[PDB]
Image 1 (tube, helix red, strand yellow):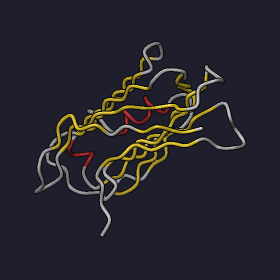
Image 2 (image 1 turned 180 degrees about the horizontal axis):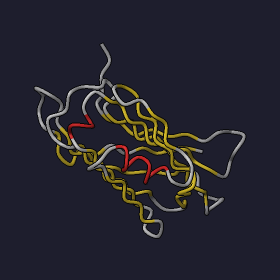
Image 3 (image 1 turned 120 degrees about the vertical axis):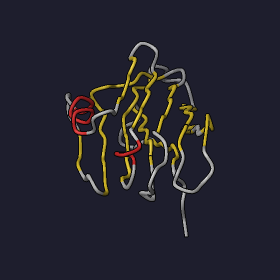
Image 4 (image 1 turned 30 degrees about the vertical axis):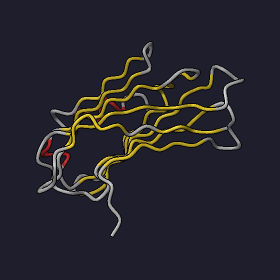
Length: 150
């Protein structure tokens, strides 16, 4: 009965007060997809993306877990046409998943940001999505932001 194609969430482990964990959860119901999936993510101020913590969990027709230092490359290799573009200076992450591979698979992209402002209480991550599930209205530029509190 539940169903949200894409949403962004995050938290702070109480045993690790210097990092914020972020999760991009794509195609949660493993629907067929009519167009490519494009996610644009802009991490906001007071935190720095830790690229070494980037992992991707794919479940469905092509179940695999990508982690380590070659994660992005191993993923882009496994999913030809896919692209994950990270800009460590700008703190942006852009994800493109071809419709053929987007179909019938859930993608959970997780990473952490190191807190650089120990005084800040809220850390926000903004994202915009472009996609279309089979038989539903096209989604374009819709915002899925999240604020982790402290």
